[PDB]
Image (spheres, grey):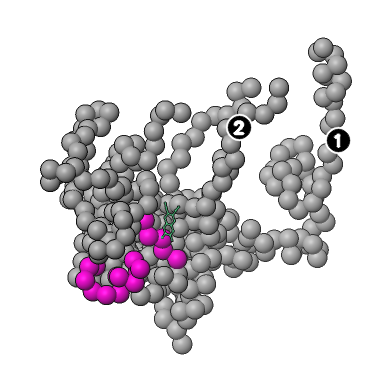
Amino acid sequence: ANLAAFLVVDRPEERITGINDPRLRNPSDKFIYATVKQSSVDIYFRRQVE
Amino acid sequence: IVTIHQEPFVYVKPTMSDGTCKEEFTVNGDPVKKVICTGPNDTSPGSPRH
Amino acid sequence: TGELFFRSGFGIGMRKDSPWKQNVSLSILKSHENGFMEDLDKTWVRYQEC
Amino acid sequence: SKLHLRVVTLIEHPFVFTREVDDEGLCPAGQLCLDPMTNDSSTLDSLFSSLHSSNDTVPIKFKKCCYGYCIDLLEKIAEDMNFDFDLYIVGDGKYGAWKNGHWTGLVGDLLRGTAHMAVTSFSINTARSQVIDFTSPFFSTSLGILVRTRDT
Amino acid sequence: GMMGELLSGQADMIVAPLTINNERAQYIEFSKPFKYQGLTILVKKEIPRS
Ligand SMILES: N#Cc1cc2[nH]c(=O)c(=O)[nH]c2cc1[N+](=O)[O-]
């Protein structure tokens, strides 16, 4: 019973999706994501106080 | 003052015939307060709605 | 069941700029923090037969 | 061409956040705020004069960039009410209570004839509502209790 | 009816569960609410499955 339940359970998957994700809403150490500095993205991606 | 009958916020109960009404108490025996209210449409129909 | 939606508040209505436009507000606040509404809510709005 | 006045406030998430200062301190998307750490009116006036002038002198530690909810709505009223504003964190962050015959916190620095407004998480009941005025409510709270979940 | 009576000047206080929306909040003045409320739904004693 335990083996069958464990086999059914295993399904990690779950790639990052979008702009509203639990992984992409708070920091950690396992998700250090970057972007080239002082360039187009980073300037805009700073004004959003939200 | 003017008040609207709508359970369970304000009740309306038949007047005890003598001139006052029932003397009841809470489950804790606390002094259930009450006043004397005259209102239309007690029964029947016309005659100033009784 | 379910959540709540379309919030509102059962105020006490009073005529425009009536002579008691303030004192009722004062008393209702001082009570509304002094554990009164909770007592009345326990004694009238909720029961425990369920 | 508009009025000039102070507003005094607090730090309680998510009403009024804190953001670490710039390279030089312009606040891209924020308001420039100052931490006095002192309940003295003349000191504050001195600091304001030093700040809005052609010769500034202030330790960088005293400057911060304030932003969030309540500041947002204050910005909407300043636009609608056509007046600029400064902003400085309160001395101690202790709300308003009676003690030793005195006041403290927001009211402590307000009834002392220092500031002109107060925007924050800030309750209203009896004692505060008597000594000083209050406006209409703009939020409807309650008291919830918190317990660690997922005992499994 | 009720609100209409309030615009008649024979009685003034209206002490009963009167809502406060903006349209009704033009001709009279209320106090700070003493009760929050909203439209809710019930279904049944939840007891599914076997
Ligand atoms: N309780 C109550 C109650 C209170 C009300 N109060 C109002 O002001 C109204 O318009 N409708 C209402 C309807 C109800 N109702 O029947 O549920």
Q: Is residue B22 left or right of residue D24?
A: left
Report x, y in % for residue D44: 36, 65
Q: Residue at x 31, y 44 (%)?
A: C37
Q: Quadrant of residue E6?
A: bottom left
Give the residue number, with chain letter if any, for mark 2. E46
Q: Quadrant of residue D2?
A: bottom left
Q: CA distance from mark 1 to mark 2?
A: 34 Å
Q: C35 and D21: which one is in front? A: C35
Q: Where are the magenta residues, as a range?
A: E1-21
Report x, y in % for residue B18: 12, 43
Q: Furthest residue to the left?
A: B19
Asked if the stretch drawn in magenta spans residue D124, the answer is: no
Position of A19 relative to E5 (above/below): above
Report x, y in % for residue D135: 35, 66
Q: Chain of mark 2?
A: E
Q: Is residue A48 left or right of residue E32?
A: right
Report x, y in % for residue B12: 29, 48
Q: Residue at x 41, y 81 (%)?
A: D3
Position of A36 relative to D48 (above/below): above
Q: Quadrant of the C terminus of chain B?
A: bottom left
Q: How many marks?
A: 2
Secondary structure type for disc 2: loop
Q: Is residue E16 left or right of residue D151?
A: left
Q: Is residue A2 visible?
A: yes
Secondary structure type for disc 1: loop
